[PDB]
Amino acid sequence: PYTIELIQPEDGEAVIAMLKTFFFKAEPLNTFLDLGECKELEKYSLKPLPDNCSYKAVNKKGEIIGVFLNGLMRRPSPDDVPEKAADSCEHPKFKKILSLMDHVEEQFNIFDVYPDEELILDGKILSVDTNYRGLGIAGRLTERAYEYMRENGINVYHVLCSSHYSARVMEKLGFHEVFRMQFADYKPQGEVVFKPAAPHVGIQVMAKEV
C-alpha cells in the first residue's frame, strides 16, 4: 500500500505540505500555545533534511503519507559549547518551545549514557496520514533508519517525544525511556510554562540500542 524511500532535497515543500495537514496542528505543545502555522516552526522542522537520513512513506500516487525526519548528532568536541536554539528565534510562542528543548539538552546528555558512541541518530518528527495509520508505517520507517544506522556505524537511535502518543509508538518498537521531564516541573522562571491536555504530561527521551 506504500513504499519507503529516502527524502530527497527536492522534497522539502512536499514535506512541509504534509506536516501542515497532519502534524503541526496536532502537536500538544503547539495546541497548548495556540501556535498556528508558523514560519520559524516550518524551517526548524526542515533543518534535518540535508543530513540525508530522513525517510518517507509514499502511496501509489507518489504522495507523501508519512515521514520520519532524522538528524545526525555528533559527539561534541571539548572546544564545542552547546547551541541555544531559543536564542536567535524571534516568534514569541515558538521560542517557548525551543527554550524547553534547550532546557532538556541542559538536563540530560544522551552522550554521557553511551560513552563509546561518537555519532547518534536523532528522530525529530514522525507523522503519518490518518488515512494510512495502523498499517505498520512507523515501524517500517524505523526499520529503514536501522539500515542507515548499520551502514554508518550508528548504534543509538534517540527520539525526544513531546507527545505521549509518539513515545508510546516508540515504546512499542522497543525503545525505552531514558529521561523524563514533567511539564508540571518545567518552571524556568519560577512558574509553569506548559500544561497541555492529558495524557501529554511531560517530555520522554526514548532510546534504542541496535
Image (tube, rainbow, N blue to C red):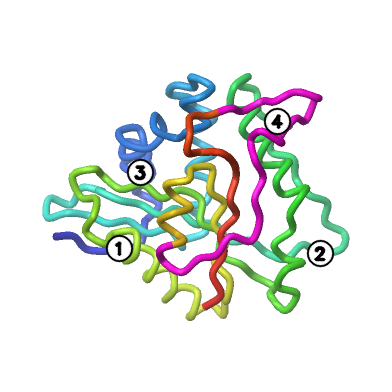
- Report the amino acid beneath label 4: Ser
Q: Is mark 4 on a helix, strand or loop?
A: loop
Q: Quadrant of the N terminus?
A: bottom left
**Residue labelled with disc 2:** 77
The circle drawn on residue 96 is none
- Report the amino acid beneath label 1: Glu
First to last magenta residue range? 172-195
Spot occupied by residue 57 in the image (x, y as percentages of width and height): 27, 57
Contact (CB < 8 A) between labels 1 and 4? no
**Residue labelled with disc 1:** 5
Q: What element carries label 2?
A: loop
| Relative to 131, 40 lies left or right | right
Which residue is the extreme one toward the right?
79
Mark 2 packing: few (<14 Cα in 10 Å), some, or many (20+)? few
**Residue labelled with disc 4:** 88
| Relative to 10, 70 lies left or right | right
Task: Work out whether mark 3 precedes mark 2 in sequence or the reverse, and give the earlier one.
Answer: 3
- Report the amino acid beneath label 3: Val
| Relative to 120, 32 lies left or right | left
Residue at left offset 51%, top offset 36%? 43
Task: Work out whether mark 3 precedes mark 4 in sequence or the reverse, and give the earlier one.
Answer: 3
The CA span between labels 3 and 1 is 13 Å
**Residue labelled with disc 3:** 15
The CA span between labels 2 and 4 is 23 Å
Contact (CB < 8 A) between labels 3 and 1? no
Residue at left offset 48%, top offset 45%? 164
The CA span between labels 1 and 4 is 33 Å
Quarter occupied by residue 44: top right
